[PDB]
Amino acid sequence: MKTIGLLGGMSWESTIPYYRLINEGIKQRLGGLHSAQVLLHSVDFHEIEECQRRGEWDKTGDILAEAALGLQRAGAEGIVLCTNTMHKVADAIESRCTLPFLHIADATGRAITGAGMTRVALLGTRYTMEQDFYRGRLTEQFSINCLIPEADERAKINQIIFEELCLGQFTEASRAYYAQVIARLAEQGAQGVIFGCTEIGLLVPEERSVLPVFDTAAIHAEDAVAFMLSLEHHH
Amino acid sequence: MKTIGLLGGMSWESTIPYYRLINEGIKQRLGGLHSAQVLLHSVDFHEIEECQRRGEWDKTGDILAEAALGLQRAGAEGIVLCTNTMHKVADAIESRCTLPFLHIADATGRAITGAGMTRVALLGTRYTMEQDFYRGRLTEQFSINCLIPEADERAKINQIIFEELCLGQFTEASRAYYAQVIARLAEQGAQGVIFGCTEIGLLVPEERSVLPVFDTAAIHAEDAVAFMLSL
Image (cartoon, rainbow over all chains, first blue to last red; front, side, top):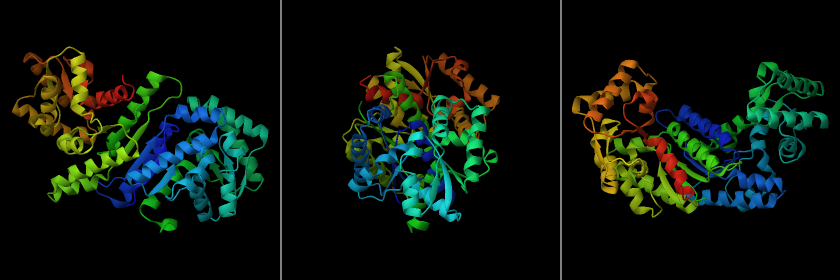
């Protein structure tokens, strides 16, 4: 199998499901005592966050590109960035490190395309929804029309994420609100909804969503397994 | 902070607590949103198992030594091997990679020294208890005496690990047997008891033991945090 390089620690809590799912996927497909060949670089999130806070995106790009080059020197054969938000600087990593870069939006784009959908909705942090680094990738590379909530909806969605979800508060009022937004975007033509992070899928079970859910973090990990085994698009 | 290099995937399930504990320890010490600077090389464990089956024991050492060299090329500043028993080949790693090798037994030696003890006991797999890779490192580097149970006790301890604990079965019959072994070791003058693996700690809560408990896996992670921060 190919050795995958993970860029993580953003946060470390969300890096663990990548490591778990990649090993579980390898263990299933190959059997026996097989486990995943993984190289992981976990950053100090404080430094990354301080850069974000100050809008120092070029600096985060340098930091992550250098981590990726380091993993390459250790023998990594592909790069997975274990965070939606930091794909803002995916272009920095791709251009400076020659390893294949497995974009989080690309993995979900292939999943959506595989289901025959052409129009979807994206729920995530406000930054992730408003920026073009995720939704622009889907449209440019997959011809997928990607709807986002309106500004008032995006602000409330964002508040719920950072004031409740990230603290472990999963309330029905918030769950209901999310369900309402999904349903409204369904009426606007969305055929599926992308959950931009784990915490949204924890709040909203699929039976509470009128649309099929794309768990973009879980899809990303599955895509990494496929890359390691040279499957499908990676064949 | 210094970047720690982890050799894991033996198993990947047991690597995760190392990662959790080092991140939590760093956050506790530095506050805010600080997390650990960590490089991890997770092996395909099947390759390790097959080296043993093929009788290529030197290759096991070479695989891990090269993994440590790879982490060193990626920026690691010390090496932690996330498994007790694979320290059987720690000499390959420590002698080929010049980064400080934070031997699992060194971490627990510092803990025991910190507690003012000179005589302890070790519970673990029969292999870990009977061979010199763990106990020898302890005594040679720290002048700490490390006793092990008598022969029938080591057999039962080992059987309980592989037949029960590794399959997620934690029975009071087995728990009581361990606690009685610990009491016997205290009678022979052990001042604390080392738990060689997490499974033993899952079976015996430290308060059930008549001796102070050194959880060697958890201490190993705490020691890495101390190294990363120069304390």
